[PDB]
Amino acid sequence: ATASSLNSVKDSLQRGQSTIDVALAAGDTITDLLTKMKEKALAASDTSLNTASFNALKADFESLRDQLQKAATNAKFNGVSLADGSTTKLSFLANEDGSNFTVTAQTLSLTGIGLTATSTFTDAATAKTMIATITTSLQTATNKLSSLGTSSVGLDTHLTFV
Amino acid sequence: SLTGIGLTATSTFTDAATAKTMIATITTSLQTATNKLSSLGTSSVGLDTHLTFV
Amino acid sequence: ATASSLNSVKDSLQRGQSTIDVALAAGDTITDLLTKMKEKALAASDTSLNTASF
Amino acid sequence: GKLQDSLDAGVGNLVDADLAKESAKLQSLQTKQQLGVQALSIANQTPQTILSLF
Amino acid sequence: GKLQDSLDAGVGNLVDADLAKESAKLQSLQTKQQLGVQALSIANQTPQTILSLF
Amino acid sequence: LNSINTNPGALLALQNLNSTNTELAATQGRINTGKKVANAKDNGAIWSMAKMQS
Amino acid sequence: LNSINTNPGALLALQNLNSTNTELAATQGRINTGKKVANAKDNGAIWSMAKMQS
Amino acid sequence: LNSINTNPGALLALQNLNSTNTELAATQGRINTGKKVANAKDNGAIWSMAKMQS
């Protein structure tokens, strides 16, 4: 029975690898959108722009922000998610006695990366501050995806060991 | 459509004094048209990205 | 294990070569600007110039 | 422009694969896979000889 | 006339891409899709080795 | 792991090949139109700026 | 040692064949992506380095 | 001698290939620059002496 019970542990570990794969697949889009928003804020920071070009960069910035929120909320695998922040942590099976393989969730929603749902710049100084804001958000996002990838690697090694 | 960019089907200038205002009117219409086209292109790029993610 | 450790060494050497490369890519600009400044000071060393050109 | 070219060279040195090594690693790994498959096919047959005893 | 020339030059700097970089990017992407098609054709065959076991 | 109904690695290779194909398609468009932001899809604000300047 | 219900050696050959399969899969993925650090699953720190510098 | 894990000759040929590639890159740099001492990396004594005489 102790040997037969390990199939559920293997299934839970590979299910966790699948959900972290979905989280990384959304995080690629989140990182590309953060890079585009950084380019938009960094372009709007220039004073030489007229009001029309600044308003156009502002509109693209808000649109990419909404697209980032949508890509964050859409990241889930059969009703569970490590990116939207819906739960602090998932506990995967690792033993016959059911001791958990912790995989802490890393929120990738705008509020979890420091941005608000209504974050935007209104003038060149606010855009210049938003450069550093989007930079810090991109940094924390890359750190979160790196932690998720390390956790998926631990899932794979534990699956081979099981 | 003309109505959506601030123009009308009857829009015209009867004399140069009105053509001088029609200049700025067509300029504002071109501005709003380019802005709406840029928003449409951004929406299409968002659809393509969500397609790849799906 | 000692062989696998060497990949980090190669990566660090590549990062150092890239840093030296950006350093020299700036240093070409420092040298050309210094040549222009020497030409400017040398042109300004003339006593024959009027106040405006100096 | 030289800065961006240098950063692209550095990120490539951080990421670009040693593809010439990868070709040899592929050519060896396919052989190792075929040898492992044949070794498993031989391993399956070892206890089947017990029927010959009866 | 000079202002229109400067405006067209600014539009070109703002929209036109440099070409010599894509001149190499194209050949590299051709080699890259060829290597990707080869890798996918290799990946298709891995499951089929199981038939030798039966 | 040892699946006959599905092979995930071939799917990952297809995703890589599709990414390379989309990159080569963007390169083909950038080469033939002579522009990095030929239309509003490429970059909305930049295309609106280029259009208003034109 | 004598056994019809199970044979440990076939299980060991299967473990080695699955290890070779994972090696060939990672290798073909490295070939078709053009990178040795394709994602955070490869190694998270170096990949975050590459993404930030990119 | 024979081994599926490591073949030294492929590594040796790859090292000679990298060496000829590096010499070819230095040759192409000497051609496109037109100088035997294009930069401080090539030869610092001649580089500095020539920059000052120039």
Image (cartoon, coloured by chain):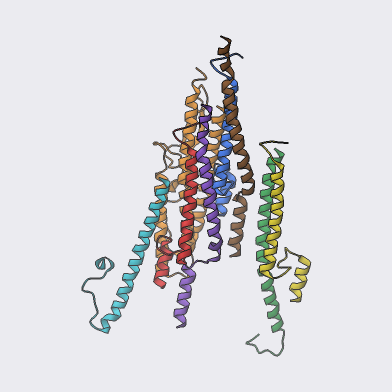
Chain colours: A orange, B cyan, C green, D brown, E purple, F red, G blue, H yellow
Residue A51 seen in the figure: no
Query: Can you say whether G39 is above or below A57 in the image?
Result: above
Q: Residue at x 72, y 47 (%)?
A: H12
Q: Residue furthest top?
A: D54
Q: Is residue B13 left or right of residue E24?
A: left
Image quadrant in which the N terminus of chain H is located: top right
Observer-nearest residue: B10 or A141? Answer: B10
Q: Residue furthest left?
A: B10
Q: Residue at x 47, y 46 (%)?
A: F15
Percent position of residue H45, x then y: 78, 67
Q: Is residue A44 left or right of residue H13?
A: left
Q: Quadrant of residue B45?
A: bottom left
Q: Is residue D11 left or right of residue B1?
A: right
Percent position of residue C24, x then y: 68, 63
Observer-nearest residue: A101 or G2? Answer: G2
Percent position of residue A98, x then y: 49, 24
Image quadrant in which the C terminus of chain H is located: bottom right
Percent position of residue A2, x then y: 51, 18
Disc count in the image?
A: 0
Q: Quadrant of residue D45?
A: top right
